[PDB]
Image (cartoon, rainbow over all chains, first blue to last red; front, side, top):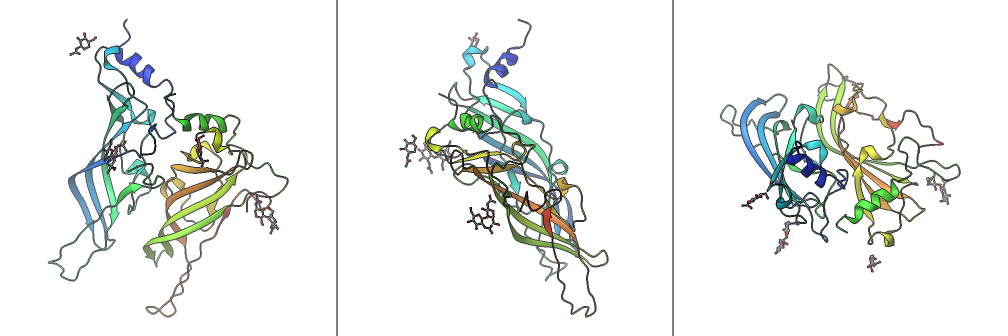
Length: 165
Length: 165
Ligand SMILES: *[C@@H]1O[C@H](CO)[C@@H](O[C@@H]2O[C@H](CO)[C@@H](O)[C@H](O)[C@H]2NC(C)=O)[C@H](O)[C@H]1NC(C)=O
Ligand SMILES: *[C@@H]1O[C@H](CO)[C@@H](O[C@@H]2O[C@H](CO)[C@@H](O)[C@H](O)[C@H]2NC(C)=O)[C@H](O)[C@H]1NC(C)=O
Ligand SMILES: *[C@@H]1O[C@H](CO)[C@@H](O)[C@H](O)[C@H]1NC(C)=O
Ligand SMILES: *[C@@H]1O[C@H](CO)[C@@H](O)[C@H](O)[C@H]1NC(C)=O
C-alpha cells in the first residue's frame, strides 16, 4: 500500500539478523574486506611533535552472508540504504594512531546494501571521511632538503586471518 | 538452517546471563584476572608538567563461570566473538592516571570466548590499545645525564581481594 517497498524489504532481511555476531555462514573461509584510501589534504606535519595530520576518504567493501534477498519479490529492488549501527561492521583500526576516540577521527552515518541473491548475501559499501593523526619518525639529517616517508598500518585488532582478511 | 551456528550458541549462553553482576558461582574464591602489557611507543616525556605519555597494547584474561557450553552441541564450536558491552568486565584502573575519561585512552570493541565445558565457564580474552598519561616524579639532579623511573599502578577501584585478584 502506501508503505514504501523498502520498508518491507528491510523488515524481511532484518528479521533474524543479529548485528553483534560475525555474519558468515560458510565452512571456514574468512570475510574479505577491501579497503580503499583517497588523500584529500595534508593538514599538518608537526616536526617537533613528530606526527602527521591527514584528511582522507575511506571506502570499505565486504559481503554480508545474512542480508541477501531476491529482487523479484520486492519490486526489482536491488539496493537499500541503512544506518551503519544496524548491521555488523569490521573493526578496522589504524595501528599507529595517536587518537583513541573514533568520534574525533571518523564520521559513519549509513551503509549501502546490494543483494547478491536470496542466499548469496549482500555486498556492503561503507563510505566516510577521516582525519588521521599518525606518529611519524622524521629523519632531519638533510633539513631543510629532507624527504620523509609516512607509514599507516591498517588491520583488525580482535579478529585474526581465519575471521577477517 | 540458514541461521549460523554461532547465532544459537549466543542465544544459549546469553539466556539467563546478567552482565551487571559479578559472574562467579564458586564458594568463596575470587576471579583471577591476568594482565599483560606491551610497550609500543613513548609518545612524550613532558618534563615541565612531569607526566609520561605511553602507547601500550593491553591483554586481560579471566574465566567467566556463567558462559560455558558443550562444543558437541554446537558443531564442535569452541570460540565465539562478542561485543565487550554484552558481558561483565572487570574495572581495571590506572591509579596514577591524569585522564579520567576512558574514551580518550582506550578502545574496547570485542571479547573472545573460549568454552571450558558446559558448567566450567569460558575463558575471556580482552585486547585493546591504550594511550596512558601517567604522572611521573622526575629527578633532574643529573640533568642532562639523568635516568628516570616511571611506575604504573593497576588494580580494581571498587572490588577487593575477595572478589577480583
Ligand atoms: C575471500 O578471498 C579468498 C582468497 O584468499 C577466496 O578464496 C578463493 O575461493 C575461490 C572459490 O570461491 C577459489 O577458487 C580460489 O582458489 C580461492 N583463493 C584462494 C587464494 O584461496 C574466497 O573465496 C573469498 N571469499 C570469501 C572468503 O568469502
Ligand atoms: C585463582 O587463583 C588462586 C590462587 O591464589 C587459586 O587457588 C588455588 O586453587 C587450587 C585449586 O583449584 C589449589 O590447588 C591451590 O592450592 C590454590 N592456590 C592458592 C594460592 O590458594 C584459584 O583456584 C584460582 N581460580 C579461581 C579463584 O577461580
Ligand atoms: C523488475 O521487477 C518488476 C517488479 O516485478 C517487474 O515489473 C519488471 O518486469 C522487472 N524487470 C526486469 C528487467 O527484471
Ligand atoms: C566435532 O564436532 C562435529 C559436530 O558434531 C563432529 O561431526 C566431529 O566428529 C567432531 N570432531 C571432533 C574431533 O570432536
